[PDB]
Length: 164
Ligand SMILES: [Cl-]
Ligand SMILES: [Cl-]
Picture 1: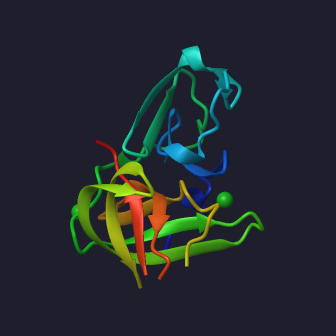
Picture 2: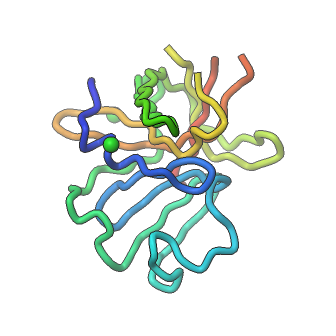
Picture 3: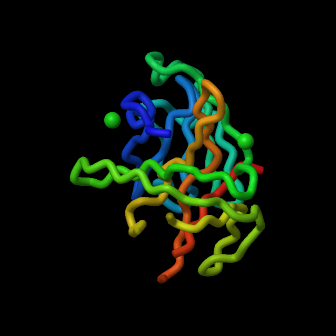
């Protein structure tokens, strides 16, 4: 299934990587790309944002509609093993590099000392800078997002962080 422009428009440069607008108020990203010590995100004070971070998965819920042009999509905790997702990688150049990935198992893993609650997959390459890119798949009418890019083997195996 081919990701349409509006879906790409959700993928947003953020910190040392990317994040993704799940809806007008909900933004997801990979914890380690998130800027630390700041007092606002997208011009909104922390106080106005509900933040939950665990297992390298970060979710922001804003009090205000930040992307009022968007519809809300389904966010799931990973996907069924065997599902082929697309990782919607934007590069700093502007290039779009959707990568097809056959997903494997969900697991709590230690990767370079960090606890990642995630899902591994095999590419059917990712680089530093790509973390936070969304893993998506289409089910019926609806695109589903089920993780954010977190790691890859040197090899090729990729891992996305998934929500509790
Ligand atoms: Cl775009
Ligand atoms: Cl499914």
